Each structure stands twice: as structure tokens, then as C-alpha cells.
Length: 162
Image (cartoon, rainbow, N blue to C red; front, top):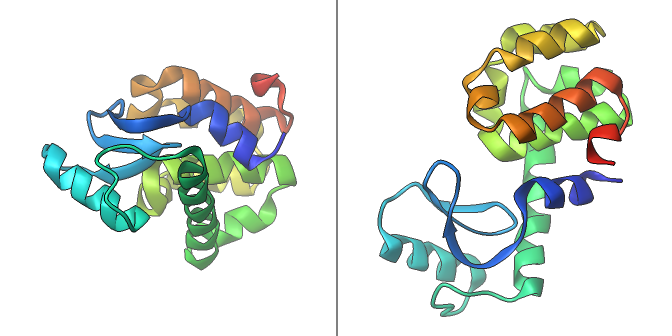
């Protein structure tokens, strides 16, 4: 298992514009297009992202490309984030993927607010962090995914992903 595989499992893959769990326009492998209600805005952002007139549809390769960019950007985001980097540096390989996953899903900023959990993670307090992590809107709104991520942080294994 690796980050791509994991995320691929958590985000699914769709070649047509779709609405995510929060109702926002997305495509590919969880690639957010816009928070705007306008499908036109979305089509626009999509064409700008891809570099051609897609008319709401893309190819698999195109999707994978955005995906690569997105994972790369999150890693980097992390590495540049003063609150996040240290955490990431203290974690083992598996747990690193769990952190990237969150960041991909919610943004560096959002993640950066999990102050208490992060601290616990830093200190290797697995179960404590897991409990704290579950006390969140995140958990309450997308429980299955959250559970997967949580478990991963909890155990340092890929069991939740089989």
C-alpha cells in the first residue's frame, strides 16, 4: 500500500464533474474544482486546470495527472507548514501517509487546527490521539473515511485498508 493507493481508495475516481460530500464541484480523484455553486464556474476552472475545453469530462490520464500534482502539493504544503512539518518528521512511514491523507482532504490550514491531536501524535500517544481525533466535525461528517485514517494513525499498519 502507498499514499496513492490509499487515497485512491478514499476518493474514488470519476471522469465527470461531480459534487463532493460537502456539495462542491470536484473531478477525478478528489480534485476540488471550486466551492462555488456555479457549474459554469466549475467548467471553467476545469478547463483552466487541464488546459483544454473539457466540457466537464476528462480522461483517466488527465485525472491521474491532477492527482499527482495534488499529492505533491500536499506533501510540500506539509513540509513548509511550521506546525505540520515537525509532526510529519516525527512519524514513521505509515503514519506519514495518514497525515498526508488528511491534508489532501482538508487543507493544511484545517489540519493545522488539530492542535491537540497533533501534539499527541508528536509524542507517540496513539490511542490518545485517536480519541481526540474522533472528536471532530471531520469524523462526524465522513465517519468511514475518518475511521480509516484514524486507525492508521492508531496502529501504524494498513489494516483499515486491507
